[PDB]
Image 1 (tube, rainbow, N blue to C red):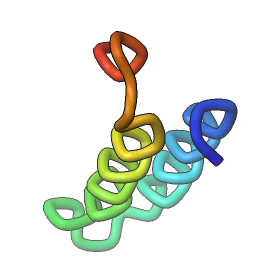
Image 2 (cartoon, rainbow, N blue to C red):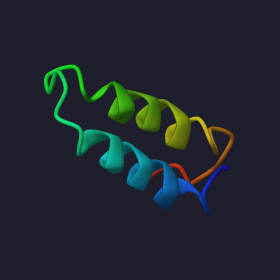
Image 3 (cartoon, helix red, strand yellow):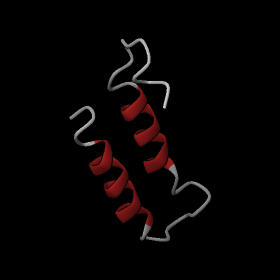
Image 4 (cartoon, helix red, strand yellow):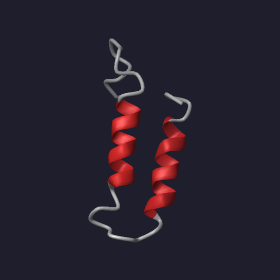
Length: 50
């Protein structure tokens, strides 16, 4: 649920973004992905940099 699913949370947000409902605010999935993936390994030295 941290970085093996860094592809999977992006793919799930992309599959939710295939639904075009409220496309300005349909990046709430992208906001949850940007919170989740960057908050996955927030304790790091360089691995969060990319």
